[PDB]
Image: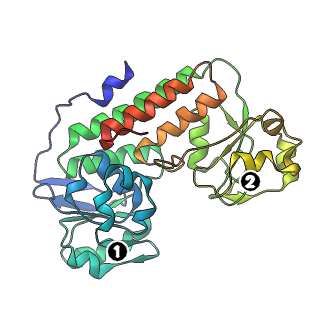
Amino acid sequence: SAFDVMSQFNEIGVSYPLTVTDQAGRTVTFEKAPEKIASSYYISTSLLLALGLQDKLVGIEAKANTRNIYKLAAPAIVSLPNMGTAKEFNTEACVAATPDVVFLPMKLKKTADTLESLGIKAVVVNPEDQSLLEECITLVGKITNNAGRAEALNNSIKTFLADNKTNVSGGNTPSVYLAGNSSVLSTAGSKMYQNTLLTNAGGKNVASELTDTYWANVSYEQILAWNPDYIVIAADATYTVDDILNDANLAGCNAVKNKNVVKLPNNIEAWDSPVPGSFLGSIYIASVLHPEKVTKDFYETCVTKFYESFYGFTPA
């Protein structure tokens, strides 16, 4: 069973002193594993929880109460000192929490210098696509002396993604419209992460020729011209499947006529950004586009096993 990889005990250790290169190219040295850890990015926080490190956290990013995964896996962390975000980093709250390491997103790269000047080790992470996420998992695993657990997480991700790609191969490749957070008219081109989820699930993006580097708006007329077989709505969208089906301006397209409209779930995590479980979004999508190859029961079992194995709770 593929699920064995999620529990495999992996005999890798870490020797200190440890010099690593972070994902901004900076060199950082650890004489031992840090015991007090701060994170100022939701992805790195999710990552730390997946490595079993909740009890070492001394600071967390803003809006922690909006993250379902903390409420299910680690609710006590929501009351930790707020480190801020790229919009505004809370330097004093960070100093006062006396962390041994702070994980920062790429957008906060200049803050690493601020923290190093104050004697605080900073590590810049950039988990913004699958390979970068996997490298970040390795990096954090090394720093925190959880390389075994990190390798199991990475193998789990690689295995299930690779299996999903093979399960869906050799038949049709349905056309798909990725609908964005703000309205059905917001969409994603090939430069976005969601496109990669979709292509690993055996679908093709009707917006592949968009050169935009983030969500971008199109017209109803363009959606009808592209005539997607399926519509997949972003996990954090404000609107729902029912909303799209009730939208008379889209009555013309295949996806609506055939009721082939779904929304990625967000009751645990949104998988349309590279959190560790994001591969589940490609399994979800495959379960919609290729249900005879990747079944709903299989998808459900993946979600349950993944969050049990790495986050210590049983999804409901």
Q: Reply above or below: 179 against 259.
A: below
Judging by the rendered image, the residue that carries numbered circle 2 is: 184
Q: Could you say whether the residue bearing mark 2 is in a helix, strand or loop?
A: loop
Judging by the rendered image, the residue that carries numbered circle 1 is: 111
Q: Residues within 10 Å of mark 2 (few under 14, many from 20)?
A: many
Q: Reply above or below: 84 against 260.
A: below
**Which residue is painted at 27% across and 75% down in the image?**
94
Q: Which of 83 and 217 is in front in this view?
A: 83
Residue at the extreme bottom: 92
Q: Could you say whether the residue bearing mark 1 is in a helix, strand or loop?
A: helix
Question: Which image quadrant for residue 113?
Answer: bottom left
Circle 1 or circle 2, nearest the eye: 2
**Which residue is painted at 62% across and 18% down in the image?**
292
The reply to whether callout 1 and callout 2 are in contact (CB within 8 Å) is no
Q: Distance between the residues labelled 1 and 2?
A: 36 Å
Colour mapping: rainbow
Question: Which image quadrant for residue 260?
Answer: top right
Q: Horizontally, is 196 left or right of 254 in the view?
A: left
Is residue 209 something that shows in the picture? no
Q: Position of residue 285 (x, y in %)?
A: 60, 35
Is residue 233 something that shows in the picture? yes
Q: Horizontally, is 10 left or right of 65 in the view?
A: left
Q: Position of residue 18 (x, y in %)?
A: 15, 53
Q: Nearer the viewer, residue 280 or 79?
A: 79
Q: Position of residue 129 (x, y in %)?
A: 48, 48
